[PDB]
Each structure stands twice: as C-alpha cells, then as structure tokens.
Length: 166
Length: 148
Length: 102
Length: 85
Ligand SMILES: Cc1ncsc1-c1ccc(CNC(=O)[C@@H]2C[C@@H](O)CN2C(=O)[C@@H](c2cc(OCCCCN3CCCN(c4nccc(-c5noc([C@@]6(C)CCCc7sc(N)c(C#N)c76)n5)n4)[C@@H](C)C3)no2)C(C)C)cc1
Ligand SMILES: Nc1nc2c(ncn2[C@@H]2O[C@H](COP(=O)(O)OP(=O)(O)O)[C@@H](O)[C@H]2O)c(=O)[nH]1
Ligand SMILES: [Mg+2]
Figure 1 (cartoon, chains in turn orange, green, cyan, brown):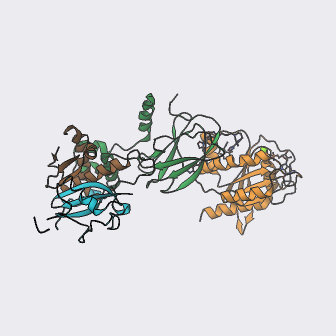
Figure 2 (tube, chains in turn red, brown, cyan, green):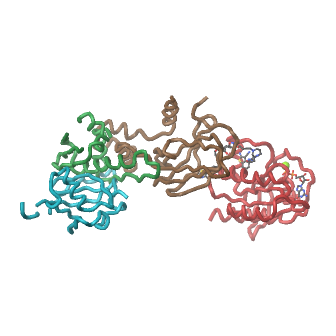
Figure 3 (cartoon, chains in turn cyan, brown, red, blue):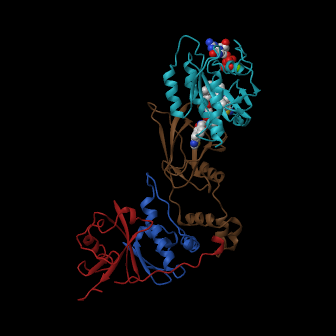
C-alpha cells in the first residue's frame, strides 16, 4: 500500500497521466476542477503493491486541512509541461510546499516532464535534469498521449518511497 | 490584529538559515495572524537554503529547551526583497545569557521537573527554575518593545 | 588574537587579558601596576617550567584555543630581597553530586 | 582600575572594574569586596563569567557556550541569584 500524489500547475496533465496509468487510455480533456484518488493494484519490482494515486486539482488553499491531506502522501510527482515555462518555474513552489508539510529537507519525489509529444519546447530536457540534481530527484520525461514513461515515473517514485523506510 | 505578524506579500525571497550555535535550532515563523508556526530543525553548524517571502517574520529557538537564540544580532529576522538573486543571510547564534539564566539552563537539563523541590536551593530559584522559556511569552514582551 | 589568563600565586588570582603578541616581560609589568612589584623580581611559571621575558605569550603555549575567556589558561607567579621562592594553593571543591542531578 | 573580590575561603580574585560591574549586587556595593557565602570555586567561575560577558556582548559573529560543570551548577546558581548578574 503506497500512497502517491500528483501535483503541478493546471494544464500540465496531472489528470492526463494518472488516467493513463490506471484506466490505460488518454482523455483529451479531463476536467481541470475535479480531484480524485484512484486505487490500483500492481506487482512493482516483485512486490504486489497497491498504488493510491491522488490526482490534485483546484485553487491554492494553505489551510490546515489541505495540508493534512497532502501530508498523507508518501511520494510526490511534480509534473510540468515542456511547452510551458511557468510550469517549470512554479516547480520550485511545488517542491517547497511539499518540504513543509512533510517536515523535511528530504522527501520522496521525482520530476516529470509531460507533453513530450508536443513539437515545440520551452524548457529543454537539459535544465530539468540538472535542477533535479540540485534536489536529489530522478527526472523522467513523460508523455501522456504517447504513454511513454508514464509507468516508470509512477514506479520509480515508489522505489524512492521504499528507500525512505530503510 | 497582532503587531508581530508576517505580511502576505506573496513575494518570494530566498534566505539562508545558518546555525552557528551549539544548539539544535528550531526556526519559528510568525503567521499572518501572529501565531508561531515551527519549522524543521537545524543541527549545530548546519546551513540550509530556505524559501521564504518578503515581510515574513521569523524567530529561532533551541529545539528542546525553547531557550532563546538570536539572528543577525537581533531577535527577529524579516527578509527584504532579494537583489540580483543574492540570498539574504540569517546567522543564528547564542545570545550572551546572564549567568543566572545560564545556570537555570544547565540545572533544568540535569534534574527532571518533579525533583526541582528536592534541591538544596533557596525557594525563589524553584519558582525561577520551573519558569521555562516559552515563546508565547517572549512575543508578548517583544510586541510591547515595539513601543518605538 | 587575544589571550585570556589568570595569574595565581599564594591565594591571589588576577583576571587579566593580554595579546598573544605580548611578551612575558610586557606581562611581568602587567603585574607591576597591580601587585606593585618589579618585572626583574617576578617569576611567571607556566606550569612547572618558567618563562624568558622575551618569549611572546603564544609560544609559551598560550593560544586563543586554550586561553579563552570562559576558561582562562593559568599562569603561576613567584616573588623574590635576594632569593626567588613556586606555590599556588588549590581552590575549594564542590560537594558530592546530588543524586537527583544524576 | 581593579577590584578585589574575596571568597569565604579566603582567595582574593582581582579582576577589572567594569567586569565586576557586570553584577548588579556588586554595583550598588561600589574599592575592595568580600563575600562569605561564595566559596573559592564558585567565585572563580563567577569571575570567568565576568570576562566572558564583556568580551562577547554585542558581538556580531558567533559566540561560544558558557560551560558549567554539573558539580558546581547549584552553588553557581545561588551566587548568580544573590549577585544579580
Ligand atoms: C527545509 C527547512 N528547514 C528548516 S526550515 C525549512 C523550510 C521548509 C519549508 C519551507 C517552505 N516555505 C514556507 O513554508 C514559507 C516559509 C514562510 O515564509 C512561510 N511560507 C509559505 O510558503 C507561506 C506562504 C506561501 C505563500 O504563497 C505565495 C505564493 C503563492 C502564489 N501561487 C500563485 C498561483 C500558482 N501557484 C499555485 N497554484 C495552485 C496551487 C498551488 C499549490 N501550491 O502547493 C500546492 C499543493 C497542492 C502541492 C502539494 C503540496 C501542497 S500542500 C498544500 N497545502 C498545497 C496546496 N494548495 C499543496 N498547490 N500553487 C503557486 C505556484 C504560486 N505565501 O505565504 C505559507 C503557505 C506557509 C521553508 C523552510
Ligand atoms: N500533447 C499532449 N497533450 C496533453 C498531454 N497531457 C494532457 N494533454 C492535454 O493538455 C491538457 C491536460 O489536461 P489535464 O490532464 O486535465 O491537466 P491538469 O490540468 O493537469 O489536470 C488537456 O488539454 C489535454 O488535452 C500530453 O501528454 N501530450
Ligand atoms: Mg485536472
């Protein structure tokens, strides 16, 4: 039973990548308002697990309630769109709020660049990997329509989670 | 509205917390309503890069004793806005405690609070000894000192 | 660099501060203005060895790392009309640690 | 300028004027002072505090902890209480 959490600015495709992971397709316009957690069961690296993916959405709320719920997460998945610069810029802010609720400098996360399918690029693959070095995180480029990497990210995140419990 | 509070500037200001004490530091943020919110601690000698915002008020305490620490030779820290992304530095340091407050510190770390009254000391000291540093009472005093 | 020291002789300990670049002699006269005694009549003994007036405070073994304000390094003093005498008398000793502080 | 502080035991601790002025109780009393309730061991660390208070007050850089050994702590607390420093 691992509890995952998917965050990133609206538009990157947090709902897109999650549905592909579970339902295995690619909704081309999932509502950007709805937030839901999906429970799936899979055998990751020989461990028949259960991944509860919480697909986050909505406006910022720094209440004691959204923090407590977000703190339940054991590994986070800060996605960003490689055609949206802001998405990347805001990555800093997403990482930092996670640090605070998890009460540590050390927290299980992996960056994820979604929408690699798209032709034009603003954020180049290069800067993302090096920023990931600045943090300690595996970077994984991903595509929600081509489905590439979708699984690895969602798996490598849980590898880190298992590592944290050692 | 409290006088010791942070301002919701929503303006990022990258700051360095640098623990130059031998105490485990507990950085405290005073929220927009003035209430003290703790944050992750810092071992002795440790330096960490913190994301905070302009106008935000911090104070720093021994994590276990809640004893008082200083930052930049004053007791509060409020970052300005950054200049050319130069980080704002926050050097935390033991203040010079009075020999009496030092001695209360040591004796509280060696005897549990039940055995204060079994010590061969004048009874004023028992009242002092169980007067543990409390941050809520240092805000009350600090706010009143903003008399300036 | 500042060095912090306490100069003991008989039952008398002087709490003065001097610079590592200060010479034992210059120090012998730091007792000149308080103990009222000549620098050619004073014998300063770091531990059981003695000191050439020329030696600077540091070489004798007095660095900031071991002559700090919160624990000044100690410096014996011996006083002469013809023959020099040393002897520091110990301080009081604390009571046995109470059990509640253990 | 200097002051002589005498312990109950009889040791005479000679430390600069301002250093002793660190003590509120030794400020109201003041060119020589005796104490009959403070042993030689407590007054020594007492005086050591005086030099530490004066070197490191309003220091911008970092300050080192004032050590107190467990055996002398309680007696030191009292002297501190009585001495008002
Ligand atoms: C390591 C360490 N060692 C010793 S200490 C220490 C340490 C550890 C952590 C830190 C982190 N620093 C702070 O805590 C600093 C320090 C002090 O200054 C106060 N403070 C603050 O952040 C304070 C503050 C923030 C602020 O925001 C002004 C800028 C905001 C402006 N907005 C504009 C809109 C776009 N957009 C946005 N749009 C929608 C959603 C989100 C979002 N964002 O998150 C989350 C998610 C869903 C993500 C998952 C995690 C959690 S959780 C939780 N509830 C969440 C939520 N809703 C989340 N979605 N974002 C942001 C990128 C930028 N104004 O005041 C409050 C919030 C606490 C600092 C030091
Ligand atoms: N080309 C491309 N488009 C995507 C991808 N993922 C999502 N989209 C589109 O971009 C938006 C993603 O929506 P959604 O998943 O709701 O983003 P959310 O805002 O993160 O919830 C939708 O307009 C999708 O049609 C992707 O990997 N590639
Ligand atoms: Mg959505």
